[PDB]
Image 1: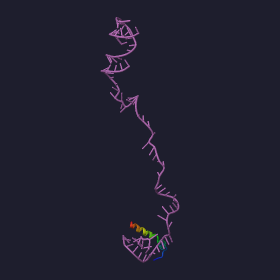
Image 2: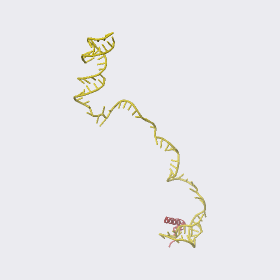
Image 3: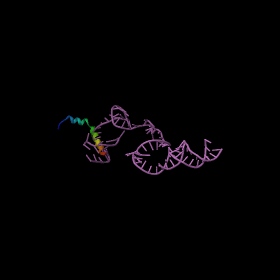
Image 4: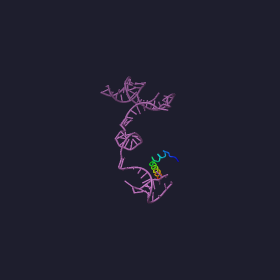
Length: 31
RNA sequence: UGAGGGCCUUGGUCACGGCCUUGGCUUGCUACAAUUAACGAUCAACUUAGAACUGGUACGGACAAGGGGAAUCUGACUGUUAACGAG
């Protein structure tokens, strides 16, 4: 394994886009 | 070429005007053209329907009800750290 800055920035800076993406997927599935 | 009207006139007749007779614009019948009258004339009819000045549109620029975010425990419970609950 390796330690890469891009992956850690992607994980840390997010936590909000992922949640809204999951909400959109659930909403469209319900529709 | 026959008829009817108009201007002429000639004799006889009755006191300029009647009566009886004599010879020279409309319409009728026939003969050759026209049938693109597919034209012209005349009488009679005919007047101007338009009003109103409503909004939603896509665009350009600020408001919009109001402190936000993440993860766990937990409650009914699908096809991705799923979702949901003003827990």
